[PDB]
Image (cartoon, rainbow, N blue to C red):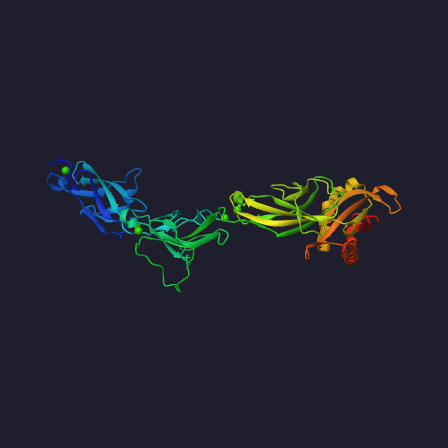
Length: 453
Ligand SMILES: [Ca+2]
Ligand SMILES: [Ca+2]
Ligand SMILES: [Ca+2]
Ligand SMILES: [Ca+2]
Ligand SMILES: [Ca+2]
Ligand SMILES: [Ca+2]
């Protein structure tokens, strides 16, 4: 005879796609091909063989015996590496004068197995290695903080259900994490009390997963990628009131009292942050007490307080009311109702209470540093030094030096919240002489004494 027919392919059937499991042993059987060459004799016996596809190297994954046609694995088959492997089979007759060949396409597709487990994916180094959620403080029960996420099981389908659970770190049980990944608030939280919480969440496919018995291996966020740190930070609300530094403030005013003079600066604190911390001040009423009297004479608005400055300022000349003092009731309020009260005592200082500080610089320059000098001095003296005026120096003899400057001041004892006799202030200066001796010279000071008899 002569090779007259080409082989034909009984199995595998035309354009078929075999499905096997993944990660099966090497050289594990897959399929047994069969083809028929009608020709009798060797011209019609078939010999099976894959084809070294040009770009497709998939054939490297299997072996097929030349006679038996049995297809066996040759490499590992991880669906996770490649899913469909595609091959072109070839059946040749042994016939002569030339053998004939027949090519049948085939494809192998792997079925997924629970090969892997749900795993997290860390963020870039340095960058925060955790996940942040935010929720308003004093939030109510149930308020969704937010949705944990960040895991994935390489697997497909049911082999990759990913449920989240809290592994450790809510010992106080402020939240609950429904497996879906929703974090719910359970308790009152107060930024001012605790600000950030944190804990470790587990990702497992086990809807019944329960934390290990507590003394077990402590966890390692650096190795276990089934774990992620989650940090909840509390947003702020206006839940804190303004709180005055003191509840009696005392400062002195001079009869000679340039209108608009800054007497003292109060302050109030709102623990709150941002707008909620904005504090606005003001004056509730003013009482005038003439020398010794138990009638609070109630003269006009004689003072002003900056709504934001907190600096009480003169509004009249007090040369009129020489004997006596004032009680100013003040208020501080936040953007939203929280309020606090206090009391300022302004006392018209007697000469007996007022001191001068001579300085060998032009008065202009003395104003240049007045604040600094006083701040330093008050610190070192540990007492409130309040600058009252800056004028040119006058010798007791009545000489006036147009390069020497005076600095009338009055002092209060933080401790007694009470004003000071010149006497006691001189003594204080002398006591601290040594500590102070540095300041005075650094600032061209020349002497100290009261309002000229
Ligand atoms: Ca043939
Ligand atoms: Ca796998
Ligand atoms: Ca798998
Ligand atoms: Ca899995
Ligand atoms: Ca707050
Ligand atoms: Ca507030």
